[PDB]
Length: 52
DNA sequence: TGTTTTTGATAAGA
DNA sequence: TCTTATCAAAAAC
Image 1 (cartoon, rainbow, N blue to C red):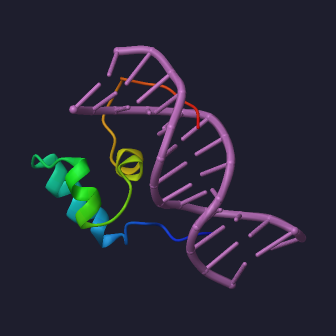
Image 2 (image 1 turned 90 degrees about the horizontal axis):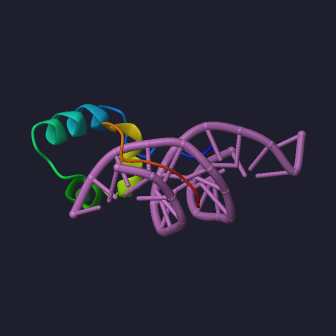
Image 3 (image 1 turned 180 degrees about the horizontal axis):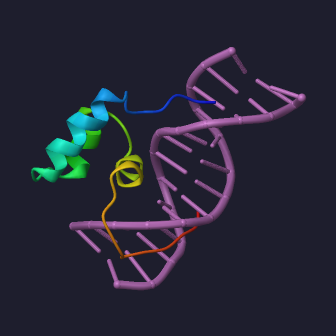
C-alpha cells in the first residue's frame, strides 16, 4: 500500500497546531499534504457529503 | 496478488 | 468559505 502522508509524530504536531487556532490551508503547504487529507485525519462536524 | 493502502481532488451539503 | 464522504489513482511493492 502507499505511505501514510503524515509521518505519525507529525499527527501530534498538527493536532496541536490546528486545535490552537491553525488553518488547514496553511498547515497543508508547509507540511505538504492536501487539505482533503488533513480534514480526513483531524475533522470536526456536520457540513457534508460526497463524490469524485 | 497486478495488488493494495492510502493520498488527494473533488462533489457535496451546508 | 467551510466540512464531508466519495473515488481514481498515486505510490509503495
